[PDB]
């Protein structure tokens, strides 16, 4: 059973701006997603200090970057805290309203899209490179869910029947046809070294041959 939801209007606006604005420095999407993963890992790590059983769903804290040329996907996997259904449907959109407004105002006053993370809405930069984003997530207190959106004002959420992931988040970027450079090992390595070299969790870049 797939449920379909409308984004908050301000978030639909933001996604349209990200999709429509001419802006060549698209590579910053990766830093933003990796930062989100790091923050999610920090959260579970801290909670585990007071309740060690929170790592019963997995003790490894890491980030994997997985390109797949045949599927034209780049997947950012973390074993962080994960998101609940309420996060996916309501809470993330609600908290993002203020940051989205501030970002759009800053852009009008001379900021650029690479500053998106300063406003707490860097996830949406995925739409610089992806025509569709699928997010598979599992929080200790909730079931495994799949969220998905191709923009256009709506997103879907369903319970995920796929491979159970233990705990964490997988952001699957279905890349646009002209954005396949982000499947290349030398390109991803370049970007991680430039913008994510000090992240406090192991980042493993998977390869293909
Ligand atoms: C569903 O797609 C998203 C949307 C629509 C918005 N932002 C985000 C970014 N985001 C947000 C995370 C979170 C959370 C809730 C807590 C309480 C952990 O802050 C969160 C978490 Cl835990 N992990 C990661 N990797 N990204 C997260 C995503 C993935
Ligand atoms: Mg919304």
Image (cartoon, rainbow, N blue to C red):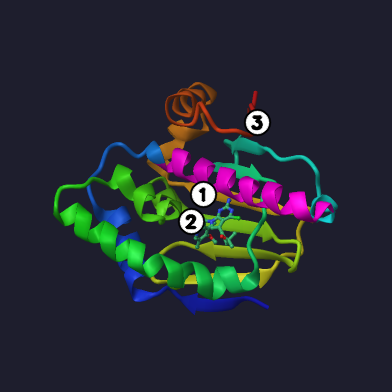
Which mark's residue is nearer the viewer, 3 or 1? Answer: 3
Q: Residue 93, how many percent across, how many down?
A: 45, 69
Left/right placement of residue 5 relative to residue 143 reads: left
Q: Secondary structure at mark 2?
A: strand
Pointer 3 residue = 202
Q: CA distance from mark 3 to mark 1?
A: 24 Å
The vertical placement of 4 against 67, above or below, is below
Give ligand 1's quarter of the image.
bottom right
Comparing 93 with 148, the one in front is 93
**Tag on residue 56?**
none
In primary-sequence order, the first of circles 2 and 3 is 2
In primary-sequence order, the first of circles 1 and 2 is 2
Which picture quadrant has residue 84?
bottom right
Q: Residue at the location (50% across, 67% down)?
A: 92
> Which stretch appears magenta?
29-52
Q: Residue at the location (59% across, 78% down)?
A: 3
The answer to whether mark 3 and mark 1 are in CB contact below 8 A is no
The answer to whether mark 2 and mark 3 are in CB contact below 8 A is no
Task: Please rate how many residues cluster around mark 3, counting C-alpha atoms within 10 Å: few if below 14, some from 14 to 19, many from 20.
Answer: few
Q: CA distance from mark 1 to mark 2?
A: 5 Å
Which picture quadrant has residue 89?
bottom right
Pointer 2 residue = 132
């Amino acid at each position: 059973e797939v449920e379909t939801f409308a984004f908050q209007a301000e978030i639909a606006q933001l996604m349209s701006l990200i999709i429509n604005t001419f802006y060549s420095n698209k590579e910053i999407f990766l830093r933003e997603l990796i930062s989100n993963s790091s923050d999610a890992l920090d959260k579970i790590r801290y909670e585990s200090l007071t309740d060690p059983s929170k790592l019963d769903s997995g003790k490894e804290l890491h980030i994997n970057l997985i390109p797949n040329k045949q599927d034209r996907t780049l997947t950012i996997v973390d074993t962080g805290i994960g998101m609940t259904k309420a996060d996916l449907i309501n809470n993330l959109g609600t908290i993002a309203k203020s940051g989205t407004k501030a970002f759009m105002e800053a852009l009008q006053a001379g900021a650029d899209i690479s500053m998106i993370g300063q406003f707490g809405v860097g996830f949406y930069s995925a739409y610089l490179v992806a025509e569709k984003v699928t997010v598979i997530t599992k929080h200790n207190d909730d079931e495994q869910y799949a969220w998905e959106s191709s923009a256009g004002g709506s997103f879907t959420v369903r319970t995920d029947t796929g491979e159970p992931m233990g705990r964490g988040t997988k952001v699957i970027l279905h890349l646009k046809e002209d954005q396949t450079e982000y499947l290349e090992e030398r390109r991803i390595k370049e970007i991680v070294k430039k913008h994510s070299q000090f992240i406090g969790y192991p980042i493993t870049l998977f390869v293909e041959k």
